[PDB]
Image (cartoon, rainbow over all chains, first blue to last red; front, side):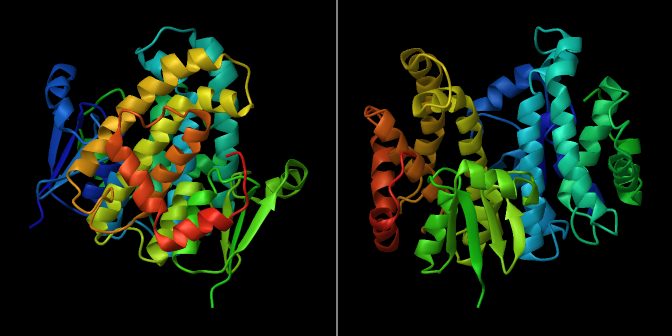
Length: 206
Length: 206
């Protein structure tokens, strides 16, 4: 009976990857959602003054990628070989690079920053989507199973589907010229235990 | 036996982590260093149109973190448990975040960008250094062995020491108020097989 505790804000964000893995493993966990004033208090207790943080029997582990990979390994969603695991990693890092590109837009659209959406939508969110999707679609075309790597689900499938689904709420024309990316989103999120989680989880705007 | 090929520019950069792991494993590998005109040719052949790329018996793997983690796992420099491996990951991601903070400065100082070094040194590099070093020193103070995690060498030890050593060539006052960070740099780079590599490797500006 390993006790898991996830500590993050009351949003999906960077904590969601972990949350979805737990659901797929049918694994109980303490889903702690902090607000700003509460986060400020525990801030110095965290390894890098940041959330999400996972605790496994009290042992702290920060960083969403490291967290989601860890659980993914623990419950068989990391990859079927050490090499495939690395390829999963490579996509997750590319996704991260892509999120750094569209930061500014992302923080401005949800309402955490000053800016013009139509400018940032035009000049930064695109081309960044195109570049990233270009690579994503390549990986899909050589997957017969529909998954990003291998003939099975891995934690990057979750990151990309979730992000795309979330972007659609802000950008309805996201995925319009990329059908392979859409069939992916739907495929992953239609998986029974994930579908169920998506329907029962707390409803938040990102 | 396993044929390894690393393809990167003629610099340490994001390819070095891998190069150092090979040295520590006493592992032969094809250290391919491209120039611009050569990179442009193979660019579309790469998973994300980018280097470094590792090939393991022909199987392509992009992204420096994924690459260095993969080899690190191969040769026992990833961590002694799946949890420790995750903590190593968390530091490597923090390092990456930190590199995004200091990017503008880094690209200006080596000569890939317009800017004022003294401005970027003062307002973006040094604060970022303090924040990051603050976390790095915390991890060291609770390590009796001197290593960042565990009682043994892992691939983050390499990333951090190498980066610090490289920064010193541009910023001589880089580790002046952080003695624990210096003892770390020296400790890692003094390890026989790494020391040897540092002395024999091609000399590049970064």
